[PDB]
Amino acid sequence: PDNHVYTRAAVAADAKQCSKIGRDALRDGGSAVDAAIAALLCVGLMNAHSMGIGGGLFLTIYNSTTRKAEVINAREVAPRLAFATMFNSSEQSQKGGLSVAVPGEIRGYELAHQRHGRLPWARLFQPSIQLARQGFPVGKGLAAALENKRTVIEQQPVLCEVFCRDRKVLREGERLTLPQLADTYETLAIEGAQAFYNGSLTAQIVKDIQAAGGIVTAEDLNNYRAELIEHPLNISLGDVVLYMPSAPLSGPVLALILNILKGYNFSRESVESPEQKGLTYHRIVEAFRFAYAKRTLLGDPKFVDVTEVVRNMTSEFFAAQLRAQISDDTTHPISYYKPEFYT
Amino acid sequence: TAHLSVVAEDGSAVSATSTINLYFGSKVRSPVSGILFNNEMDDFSSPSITNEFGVPPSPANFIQPGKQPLSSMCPTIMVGQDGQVRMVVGAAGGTQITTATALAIIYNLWFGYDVKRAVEEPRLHNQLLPNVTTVERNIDQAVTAALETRHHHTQIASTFIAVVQAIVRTAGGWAAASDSRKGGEPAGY
Ligand SMILES: *[C@@H]1O[C@H](CO)[C@@H](O)[C@H](O)[C@H]1NC(C)=O
Ligand SMILES: *[C@@H]1O[C@H](CO)[C@@H](O)[C@H](O)[C@H]1NC(C)=O
Ligand SMILES: *[C@@H]1O[C@H](CO)[C@@H](O)[C@H](O)[C@H]1NC(C)=O
Ligand SMILES: *[C@@H]1O[C@H](CO)[C@@H](O)[C@H](O)[C@H]1NC(C)=O
Ligand SMILES: *[C@@H]1O[C@H](CO)[C@@H](O)[C@H](O)[C@H]1NC(C)=O
Ligand SMILES: *[C@@H]1O[C@H](CO)[C@@H](O)[C@H](O)[C@H]1NC(C)=O
Ligand SMILES: [Cl-]
């Protein structure tokens, strides 16, 4: 049993130190966006295997004064020289510079901070600059990720540079220091986002990616833009609305899952006995299967027309039609759910 | 992928999911800047690549210059009719992000589990292909049995299924939870 209830405000991040960093930003007068950015910068250090300024993000943001939700799209984008047949194996699409898409992270932070920031840009970086220099004990998640990838990490000395102690990956509890990223964070704090996309970091970024066999160019970085989505996806759930990003993210899938299940009117009773509980969980799995059948039509809506697909995936009536094909006593083969690769 | 959830004192909120894709992304680290580059290109489908036996590639998610690849991420915010936030939730982990986010919601909103239980409760996943239901190792085994008698094939997750960070409004304020599977804890005041 481990509850955390707060009267005024809260941050839930995947490392305690980053939650605290977000919390302190709030306490110093920051917006929810300030806190999120400060915390994200920290998670990029403490769970560096999972996210960071070399990646991309989406933020769903709700303003309680205007009661409006918005989405900020800062996901990476295929470089200008990319093409459909550029990879011939999975290993090619996964390792090395050619697997790299144009990072959107910092630009996402910028747009969000531009629209909703209260604290100065540099203030958001300060705690993480310190942390990366001081170092920190390796947490549970990062340790398991290090073990999982120990072979690759130990064979690539630029990664072993920071992620190993004496040629072997760091273990939980052992200190991790990230002195180069600390300097880079400092540059970003002082020179702003421009340093990444069109400034002092840019040539080096391009050099590192091309040296590893990639094709990202300076122009790709100069041209990257985070996007504001003023009308994100929503569905009604009883007396509530649920705001989530549409394609290219999986809001449409989530929406369909929940719209299928809402017609069963689940409550506490749904899990009070083994018989009810078993049927409830079967129903969940079948909702998953139907929703995943439709997922294969989704893609970037700037490049593919997903208007009608998403309209179906968020329609309660369409969902009810799928729910009526869920059999209480059996699951079905793949084709029953009508997976679709073309409209 | 990494998910975090935030609610400020004025009731405004942020749900944020961020990613470099696979563990350590492309495995390319800059020796000068220390930046670890994503391998987000792996999230496109390619006519030349087969990821599952019998699964064809998805033309809608083919690589084109300037296009964004499909993502499992879904940072979500649920708000009540009175304009006040009810839930801030999202997840990280794999293809299981979407299903785990749905479960967190179902668990809290419908089964009545408090936010920590909703985060800690065992999860399961099915994504049509592969044709198997993955369950976490401490799932109620009556559920496993109920699934198999209905002809599902179940398999036990070697590690864990997804990672969920959540905040929910309660009478006592804002209850927050981070997922023990990854080792987080929240903070607030
Ligand atoms: C894969 O094959 C195509 C077609 O010949 C080629 O254009 C591309 O460069 C190849 N990619 C790699 C990484 O070898
Ligand atoms: C919320 O909306 C109000 C009214 O438009 C605006 O003045 C305020 O700056 C917004 N809050 C943030 C953090 O952007
Ligand atoms: C900055 O942008 C301009 C045009 O946007 C370009 O000419 C210049 O080379 C860029 N500088 C860097 C370092 O990318
Ligand atoms: C949800 O659906 C669409 C989104 O574009 C819009 O017509 C409607 O206003 C949205 N509802 C809310 C409560 O934001
Ligand atoms: C939307 O759903 C209807 C059934 O309700 C179906 O006839 C139609 O083909 C669907 N549209 C797409 C693009 O799948
Ligand atoms: C998938 O699993 C179901 C579950 O019993 C089974 O009916 C079906 O034959 C399996 N294979 C396919 C291709 O659906
Ligand atoms: Cl996470």
Image (spheres, helix red, strand yellow):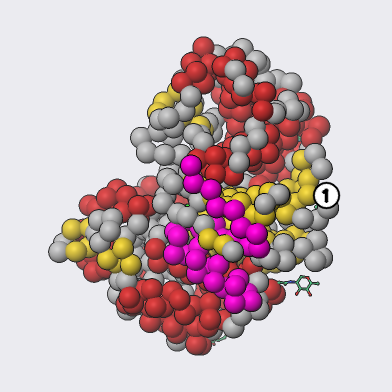
User: Which part of the image, by quadrant, shows the C terminus of chain A?
Assistant: top right
- On screen, residue B148 versus residue B5, left or right, reads left
Among the 4 quarters of the image, the one containing residue A45 = bottom left
According to the image, label 1 marks what residue?
B81
Residue A255 visible in image? yes
Is A28 contained in the magenta span?
Answer: yes
Is residue A13 positioned above or below A322 on the image? below
Residues A188 and A280: in front is A280
- Amino acid on which disc 1 is placed: Gln
Q: Residues within 10 Å of mark 1 (few under 14, many from 20)?
A: few
User: Residue A18: x and y, percent?
Assistant: 47, 65
- On screen, residue A96 versus residue B113, left or right, reads left
Residues A343 and A143: in front is A143
User: Residue A132: x and y, percent?
Assistant: 36, 73
Q: Residue at x 66, y 16 (%)?
A: A327
Is residue B151 positioned above or below B54 on the image? above
Residues B117 and A122: in front is B117
Q: Residue at x 81, y 32 (%)?
A: A317
Q: Residue at x 60, y 32 (%)?
A: A288
Q: Residue furthest left?
A: A166
Q: How many marks?
A: 1
Judging from the image, mark 1 belongs to the subunit labelled: B
Residue B75 visible in image? no
Residue range corresponding to the magenta coloring: A1-30
Is B92 contained in the magenta span?
Answer: no
- On screen, residue B152 versus residue A265, left or right, reads left
